[PDB]
Image (tube, rainbow, N blue to C red; front, side):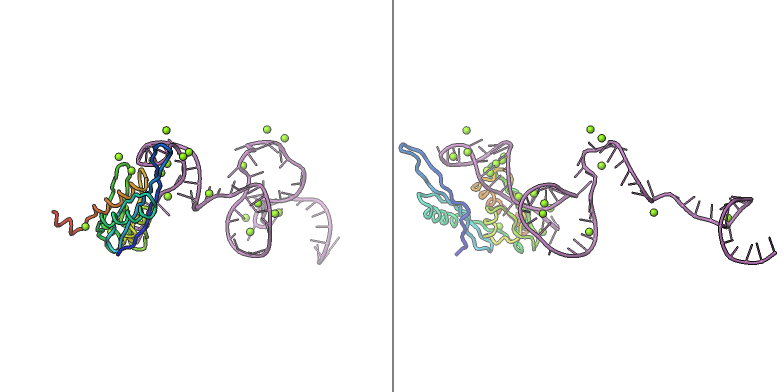
Length: 148
RNA sequence: UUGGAGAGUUUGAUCCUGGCUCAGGGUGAACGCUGGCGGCGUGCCUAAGACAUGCAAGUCGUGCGGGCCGCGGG
Ligand SMILES: [Mg+2]
Ligand SMILES: [Mg+2]
Ligand SMILES: [Mg+2]
Ligand SMILES: [Mg+2]
Ligand SMILES: [Mg+2]
Ligand SMILES: [Mg+2]
Ligand SMILES: [Mg+2]
Ligand SMILES: [Mg+2]
Ligand SMILES: [Mg+2]
Ligand SMILES: [Mg+2]
Ligand SMILES: [Mg+2]
Ligand SMILES: [Mg+2]
Ligand SMILES: [Mg+2]
Ligand SMILES: [Mg+2]
Ligand SMILES: [Mg+2]
Ligand SMILES: [Mg+2]
Ligand SMILES: [Mg+2]
Ligand SMILES: [Mg+2]
Ligand SMILES: [Mg+2]
Ligand SMILES: [Mg+2]
Ligand SMILES: [Mg+2]
């Protein structure tokens, strides 16, 4: 099993005669703090089901981060629409320096030491997607020598 | 490679653009309430407006001639 954290829980509305009627969403990451994270987005008529629905997707889309002594191997800059995330490798006693969104994403991934920065649209849902697709594009010296 | 966190606010709801605003550190500071000791710094940022009084540049008789006073003694 994994450690699980709810990063976002929001309410949205739609309109029809008689007035507004709501729907809830939850951005949820899940991970072992040992090289495995997954991000899931769940929407439902009530908070709990959405949180649970989210968790199922989180496990449905996962990714394997090549941790090297608790930091990422190389620079990664990634855009997701108008959102940009910078992940920069950091030495031992550094700490995890990121906003509560990529913080929880990287944290549950076993990342213990990292310099980061959000640029552009800091919309919670998009910055999430950009942090993940960044990891999914992380490589190591092995991976490289094998390609080339 | 010793180094980089963001949030609030346009919408019924969304994504984006965009500004406004905030949390930080800093100061020869000032103001309010309050105020026990000590150490080290430090204190007219305005009128280079105006200033009472004292003090801040003198020293040498191993350059010279003197006046006064004194010790000496003619
Ligand atoms: Mg890999
Ligand atoms: Mg772009
Ligand atoms: Mg975006
Ligand atoms: Mg390195
Ligand atoms: Mg912007
Ligand atoms: Mg924003
Ligand atoms: Mg660098
Ligand atoms: Mg910041
Ligand atoms: Mg408003
Ligand atoms: Mg409008
Ligand atoms: Mg409103
Ligand atoms: Mg803004
Ligand atoms: Mg201040
Ligand atoms: Mg005072
Ligand atoms: Mg007083
Ligand atoms: Mg003193
Ligand atoms: Mg002056
Ligand atoms: Mg005048
Ligand atoms: Mg006058
Ligand atoms: Mg004097
Ligand atoms: Mg002489």
